[PDB]
Length: 228
Length: 4
Length: 50
Image (cartoon, rainbow over all chains, first blue to last red; front, side, top):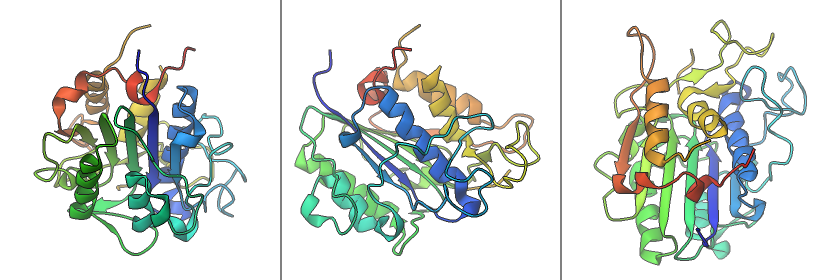
């Protein structure tokens, strides 16, 4: 049996009620990983945190990631929220460097060489770029550089990256080398959209008055699969 | 559907 | 009850996300060290004994 520690970094790259789904994706991922036995101290959550009590939310204080889903917001730690959701903090977290963090909980992936790491990002994207709710945006070269650095630190056995965004293939295609012990998958290729799901007017639809999608198809595809 |  | 690998989840996710009837959809990709995908999901996401 695996004797290493399992870590995760969960990142919603957007803000605003219309982007409900990205923070819902991340909260769902948090609950799933906790149910799997990952410890709270090893799961680092980035979310702007403007959804659960958004005035447009039909169910104040809750977030759901499927039409009949349970609340997934309760229990999610507020590691990096609001303007603490930024690239410098994300990189400090991935590299396990508490002294490079600015604002937020200070939780980082201070991992060892026999540990596993799971990173899940959900948001908006375009060719070569991922959204953040603060300046600057998360650029493909910068993200791949920080993964290379982490590999140079040697502080994991293997790392898995799941990525939800438009043109998300562009973030790794021809940029992520073999030999880093990193496996990544993306919702889309480098030239096409990725899609929300559980959207008004579509089947199945969110409850009345949500007027926003509850999740993203690639994201709920893996999370609902892991559940069953 | 909304795109990302 | 069965073991699931990263590769098996990738295939399942790819299938659900793919366009059908040439409407919407997207094409799930994989990158990096694909050999890793033989790993059991439990190595990354744990096990909910359920």
